[PDB]
Image (cartoon, rainbow, N blue to C red; front, side, top):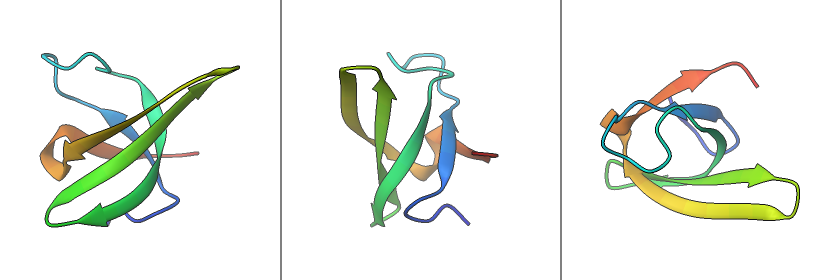
Length: 57
Protein backbone atom coordinates (compact mmCIF):
# COMPACT_ATOMS: atom_id res chain seq x y z
CA UNK A 1 0.00 0.00 0.00
CA UNK A 2 3.11 2.19 -0.04
CA UNK A 3 3.11 4.07 -3.34
CA UNK A 4 5.04 6.95 -4.92
CA UNK A 5 3.87 10.13 -3.19
CA UNK A 6 2.97 8.40 0.06
CA UNK A 7 4.51 9.53 3.34
CA UNK A 8 6.30 6.85 5.34
CA UNK A 9 8.14 6.55 8.64
CA UNK A 10 11.29 4.45 9.01
CA UNK A 11 10.83 1.74 11.64
CA UNK A 12 14.28 0.07 11.69
CA UNK A 13 16.08 1.05 14.92
CA UNK A 14 19.41 0.15 13.31
CA UNK A 15 18.92 2.75 10.57
CA UNK A 16 20.34 6.27 10.51
CA UNK A 17 16.91 7.63 9.66
CA UNK A 18 14.93 5.69 12.25
CA UNK A 19 11.61 7.49 12.91
CA UNK A 20 12.26 10.07 10.17
CA UNK A 21 9.30 10.67 7.84
CA UNK A 22 9.72 11.17 4.11
CA UNK A 23 8.01 10.99 0.72
CA UNK A 24 8.16 7.81 -1.36
CA UNK A 25 9.78 8.57 -4.72
CA UNK A 26 9.53 5.12 -6.28
CA UNK A 27 8.83 1.51 -5.39
CA UNK A 28 10.31 -1.55 -7.08
CA UNK A 29 11.51 -5.05 -6.26
CA UNK A 30 10.13 -4.83 -2.74
CA UNK A 31 12.08 -1.66 -2.01
CA UNK A 32 11.26 2.04 -1.93
CA UNK A 33 13.36 5.16 -2.40
CA UNK A 34 12.40 7.76 0.20
CA UNK A 35 13.24 11.46 0.19
CA UNK A 36 13.77 13.14 3.56
CA UNK A 37 13.71 16.93 3.73
CA UNK A 38 14.37 19.69 6.25
CA UNK A 39 15.08 23.17 4.92
CA UNK A 40 18.09 23.03 2.61
CA UNK A 41 18.93 19.53 3.79
CA UNK A 42 17.71 16.40 2.05
CA UNK A 43 18.66 12.77 1.64
CA UNK A 44 17.44 10.05 -0.71
CA UNK A 45 17.59 6.57 0.79
CA UNK A 46 16.36 3.19 -0.42
CA UNK A 47 14.72 0.86 2.11
CA UNK A 48 13.17 -2.58 2.03
CA UNK A 49 9.41 -2.14 2.43
CA UNK A 50 9.64 -3.92 5.81
CA UNK A 51 11.63 -0.94 7.14
CA UNK A 52 8.80 1.49 6.36
CA UNK A 53 5.26 2.09 7.59
CA UNK A 54 2.65 4.32 5.98
CA UNK A 55 1.61 7.47 7.84
CA UNK A 56 -0.53 10.56 7.24
CA UNK A 57 1.14 13.38 5.23
